[PDB]
Amino acid sequence: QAQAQNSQYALARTFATQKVSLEESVLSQVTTAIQTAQEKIVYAGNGTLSDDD
Amino acid sequence: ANRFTANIKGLTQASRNANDGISIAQTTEGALNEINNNLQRVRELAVQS
């Protein structure tokens, strides 16, 4: 009985890790994208830009 | 670490902004020098007149 409990939680941990890693990946890329959008915003602050640029 | 990265990138682009400013300012300075020279010659002529 005890062994059965342990095995079931092995499986649960397997699937939890699946989802966790899959999130982390796109989350890192989201950080990247936020940062690039930030940089191009800071360039919008450039006080020499013409309207077409 | 991610916060550090964010600040680094922002600061670099801000430095580029500062250079944009120096460029525009120097163009204005260049033009104003010629304005000044012309005004000096005009004062010279007014003196002659």
Image (tube, rainbow, N blue to C red):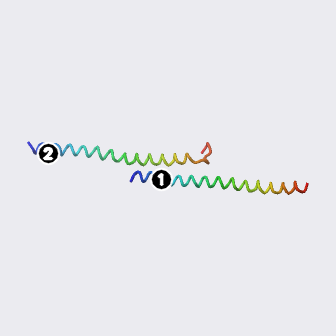
Can you identify the residue that label 2 sits on? A6
Say which element carries label 1: helix
Q: Is the residue B20 above or below the residue A19 in the image?
A: below
The chain carrying label 1 is B
The chain carrying label 2 is A
Residue at 40% x, 51% y is B2
Quarter occupied by residue A19 = top left
Q: Is the residue B48 above or below the residue A26 in the image?
A: below
The CA span between labels 2 and 1 is 48 Å
The answer to whether B41 appears left or right of B6 in the picture is right
* Front residue (pair A31, B6): B6
Disc 1 residue type (three-letter)? Lys
Residue at 24% x, 43% y is A15
The answer to whether A28 appears left or right of B34 in the picture is left
Locate residue A43, reporting x and y percent: 54, 48
Can you identify the residue that label 1 sits on? B9
The answer to whether A51 appears left or right of B40 in the picture is left
Locate residue B14, reporting x and y percent: 53, 52
* Front residue (pair B37, A37): B37
